[PDB]
Image (cartoon, helix red, strand yellow):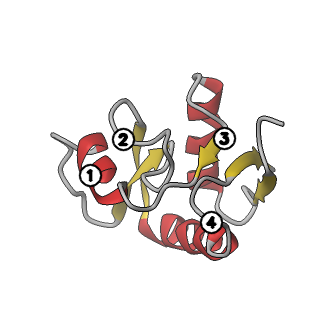
Amino acid sequence: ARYDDILYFPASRYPETGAHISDAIKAGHSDVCTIERSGADKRRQESLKGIPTKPGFDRDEWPMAMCEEGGKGASVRYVSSSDNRGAGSWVGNRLSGFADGTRILFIVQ
């Protein structure tokens, strides 16, 4: 009852993103994303304040900006763009049908 559905994140396919999710969760950041898409732009901005872009890398956020849990205090790490683009799309496609408020537990595999 602390989540509605599970996603098994495929660390074998996206090991650099997957390593950050695991470290961030191991660090205490929530393993549940409660989906909240309206306030994502502002969370993104909050989490990355003071962090410059880096060539060939994306600034990866856990919890993610699309989650209630995201934003200020989110773990940020530069992850290689290929890895993080694929991870992003995998997650995005899997969550696209869940309504805001749906609580998703992430297990990194």
Q: Give neighbour class at mark 4: few <14, some 14-19, many 20+ (Cα, 10 Å).
A: few
The answer to whether residue 58 is left or right of residue 10 is left
Q: Which residue is mark 4?
A: 99
Task: In the rendered structure, find residue 42 and report the number of the disc placed on it.
Answer: 1
Verify CB contact (< 8 Å) between mark 1 and mark 4.
no
Disc 2 designates what residue?
A: 71
Determine which residue is flagged by label 3: 32
SS category of the residue bearing label 2: loop
Q: Earlier in the sequence, mark 2 or mark 1?
A: 1
Q: Residue furthest top?
A: 28
Q: Is residue 62 left or right of residue 42?
A: right
Secondary structure beneath label 3: strand
CA gap between label 1 and label 3 equals: 20 Å
Q: How far apart are the alpha carbons under marks 3 and 2?
A: 14 Å
In the image: residue 41, left or right of residue 50: right
Q: Nearer the viewer, mark 4 or mark 2?
A: 4
Q: Mark 1 or mark 4: which comes first in sequence?
A: 1
Give the image location of residue 75, x and y in percent: 43, 35
Q: What's the residue at 77%, 43% (across, down)?
A: 3
Question: Callout 1 environment at 10 Å: few (<14), some (14 to 19), or many (20+)?
Answer: few
| Residue type at numbered disc 2 | Gly
* Disc number lying in front (1 or 4): 4
